Amino acid sequence: AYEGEPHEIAENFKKQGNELYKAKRFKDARELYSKGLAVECEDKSINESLYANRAACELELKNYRRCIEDCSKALTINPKNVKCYYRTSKAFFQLNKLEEAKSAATFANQRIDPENKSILNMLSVIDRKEQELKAKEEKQQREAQERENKKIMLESAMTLRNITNIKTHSPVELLNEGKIRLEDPMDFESQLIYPALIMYPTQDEFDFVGEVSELTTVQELVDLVLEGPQERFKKEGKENFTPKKVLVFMETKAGGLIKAGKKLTFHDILKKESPDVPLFDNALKIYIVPKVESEGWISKWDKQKALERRSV
Ligand SMILES: [Mg+2]
Image (cartoon, rainbow, N blue to C red; front, side, top):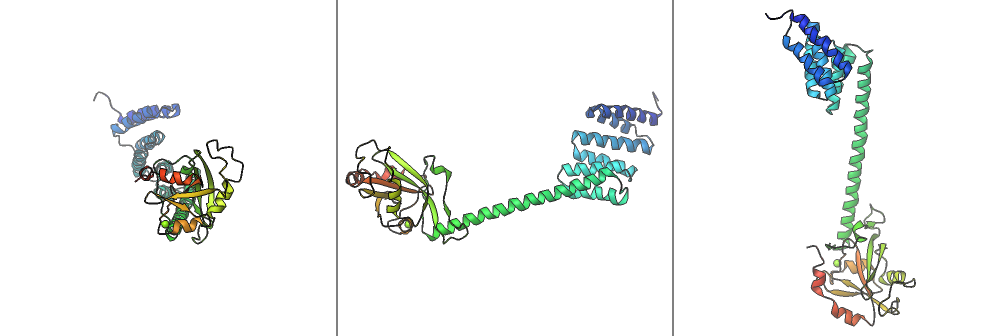
């Protein structure tokens, strides 16, 4: 009664809102279209445009479900509005629902306008995203399977060789990289290769050789590390450090010690039931000491000092 001609009031809000979509602030444009809808005039083309325009505002705002609903209401008035099918398709695409995106664009392509360029582009974009996700899936899943194949083959190898691995709370930073493998990583009968902490406790110095084959003997590893002239051994008894004059010792699972025989391989040492000589942090830990200082150093070995280096 205060004011009427609601069809022109609806077009007032419609034309007023279209200048704001050109102006780019969408939340104000969006609400201006809503008031044209609230008038509820008996006119199809006005209401169709209001629903299609508000859907466009919701797409720019990135409210994708609300965009689909305003497109649906526009298509109830005009089911051959190709603009609304593009927006439903793009909205579904952005929600990672590619089948719902393809269905809408396929309906527009097959049954409304095959020549429409925005619908064809959306088809090609849906097509690419479908198969790029496939290439991503069949890369992720093969690599997880390959990772798992390497891990089972390594555990089988270590269980077969009777190797116990006792982890410690404080490994020095060279060990924490973690380098243990098979030569043929799919054949668990090929050589297991592990790193080695070589301890010289009398001098307070250590070597870290990154890769030692299991079939390597104790003598051969001792020959390699002591070959060069030692700049390192400043403390007492430096002259005794030669392959002929040193002895090699290793920690047991109980916490004590065993003299590692120079003829023996690391394979045969780790495999033995008694005494059980394990790895520490997936690596060897040997103690090279002079032959003359071994008697005093073995007595010094504290059993609980070593027992409480361990994690659990
Ligand atoms: Mg053993």
